Image (cartoon, rainbow over all chains, first blue to last red; front, side, top):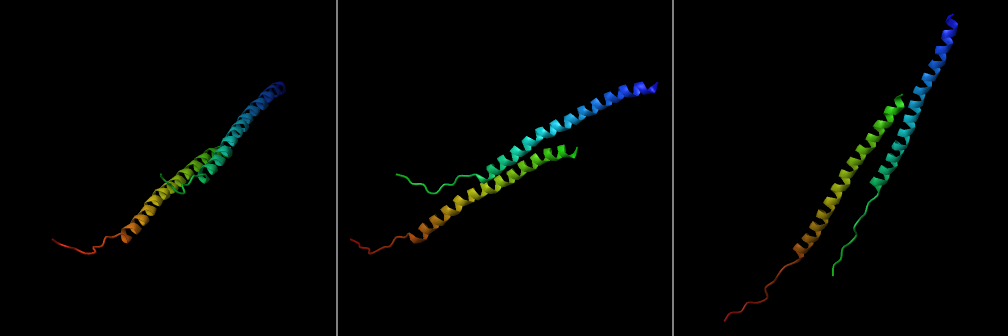
Length: 58
Length: 58
């Protein structure tokens, strides 16, 4: 009967959907750390600087 | 999955803002030295002079 064949494919459908879910989570986690670090590094880059007061010679 | 594309463009937005920041700082530093030197050179120019006391002939 059709009942047996339906159950077999059902298991396969669940496993496939889990794979695509894993890709999206892993990619978002990788891009999270890069975007956070870039923002913090740029903030330090703009604000920091050195200034010359006076120059003397002998 | 709108979250993925958001993070990618975010990185680019930060980098562009850093470029425009650099231009303004570099230009102000260049104009600083010219404006300082011109003031001091003019102060010397106005105040300095020579005077003739007396002239004799033989």
